[PDB]
Amino acid sequence: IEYATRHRARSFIPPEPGKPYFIEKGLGDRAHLFGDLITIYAGGEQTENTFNFFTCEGPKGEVIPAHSHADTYEVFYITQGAVRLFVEDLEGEQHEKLLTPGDFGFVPKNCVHAYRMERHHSQVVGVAAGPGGTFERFFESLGTPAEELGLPVRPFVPEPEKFRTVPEQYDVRFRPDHQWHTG
Amino acid sequence: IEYATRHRARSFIPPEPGKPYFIEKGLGDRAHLFGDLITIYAGGEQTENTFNFFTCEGPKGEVIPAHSHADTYEVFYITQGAVRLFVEDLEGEQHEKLLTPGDFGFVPKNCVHAYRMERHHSQVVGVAAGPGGTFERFFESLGTPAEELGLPVRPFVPEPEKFRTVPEQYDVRFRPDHQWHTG
Ligand SMILES: O=c1c(O)c(-c2ccc(O)c(O)c2)oc2cc(O)cc(O)c12
Ligand SMILES: O=c1c(O)c(-c2ccc(O)c(O)c2)oc2cc(O)cc(O)c12
Ligand code: NI
Ligand code: NI
């Protein structure tokens, strides 16, 4: 049976801290953002705002917007398909790598980065957290929560206003002028 | 690409915090504990002691020792095989679930728990962290660090004294007399 939480009328994440739980494949809290489906299995409420756990999956596509996080560190661990990760270090040097399932990428705070899914229905396991809390409700805030299972039929394109206001609540800084010179 | 660190003569985890990095499948810092191989991709040094990221893989086996963590929350995210997760909640009710790849289990602090791998070379993605810091160097401390790739050839059984002294440094509390009555 399911739970009612702060985030969903129907969720498999228990609302109270301190409760163990299991969630079958795909049934975490879901959000749509562009063509991608984000699925949250644990958030800050579960971990005293220490860490989170979520997956991101999507169609073969182009790079997501280049961005950074001032106080948040991010893991990319590939589970399906192939994902090209772009990252610029603090010294301005850029790096790219095609990550295949079981490969790992790590993006520290203040490092500009982006990714491109290079196979249909690629999937990434992510953790996104830091001294300033956990990041997981970003996705449904800029994008939209989803009740349906599976990849969105139509991409969810946030209205411009969302891109201005979501940084006020979530640790994200967009870098639309950023150019990748790794090819 | 390879570094000497506080933890290993050779590592693909950079010693300097704030550096982006990639690690190919299997090439995180490795440790053996019983028949299992633990591979660390990010530790507390990478995240200001906020979270970590590791895998655990091993043969079809019996349940690991029942234990709890006083300040640490743990994620079980199955990537290969099938893994049965046992957990006792704070009110003493026990639960078990066979978790298959893509399935998720969450064990809050102070819940007694254990797992059993039920396919050869099953694999779990883990995060284990909390207000008490990050847990990942526990495995090489009770077990042993490993330079070679692959499952350990001989199980590493820790001497009884390590079970007494490792809890003084890592957030783990063994429950040697704990009995699972879930099936
Ligand atoms: O800022 C973003 C972000 O951080 C993540 C992300 C995805 C997978 C991970 O594994 C991870 O650690 C982070 O996705 C995004 C997707 C967007 O369309 C826009 C974004 O701004 C982000
Ligand atoms: O205390 C332990 C522990 O926490 C974990 C663990 C394993 C995979 C995970 O994904 C995770 O979150 C935790 O494994 C163990 C394995 C042992 O042989 C003995 C232990 O004492 C632990
Ligand atoms: Ni990001
Ligand atoms: Ni544990």
Image (spheres, coloured by chain):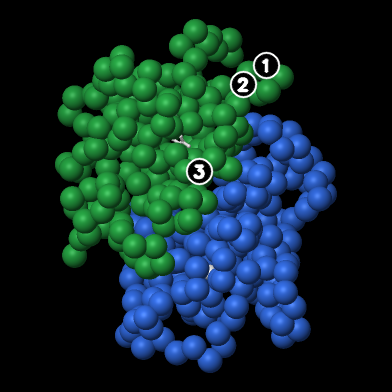
Chain colours: A green, B blue
Quadrant assignment, res A103: top right
Give the chain letter at badge 1.
A
Relative to A145, B99 lies left or right? right
Task: Identify the residue at image location x=44%, y=39%.
Answer: A135
Can residue B32 be seen in the rendering of this structure? no
Separation of disc 3 and disc 2 at Cα? 23 Å
Is A129 placed above or below B77 here? above
Q: Are marks 1 and 2 in contact (CB under 8 Å)?
A: yes
**Nearer the N terminus, badge 3 or badge 2?**
2
Q: Check residue A88 in the rendering and tell me which mark sits there, or answer none.
A: 2
From the Cβ of disc 1, is ligand 3 less than 8 Å away?
A: no
Give the chain letter at badge 3.
A
In the image, A152 versus A51, the foreground residue is A51
User: Is disc 3 surrounded by few (<14), some (14 to 19) or many (20+) residues within 10 Å?
Assistant: some
Give the chain letter at badge 2.
A
Quadrant assignment, res A94: top right
Q: Position of residue A101 (x, y in %)?
A: 47, 41
Please determine if labels 1 and 2 lie on a single subunit: yes
Q: Amino acid at mark 3?
A: Gly
Q: Amino acid at mark 2?
A: Glu
Q: Check residue A133 in the rendering and tell me which mark sits there, or answer none.
A: 3
Quadrant assignment, res B183: bottom left
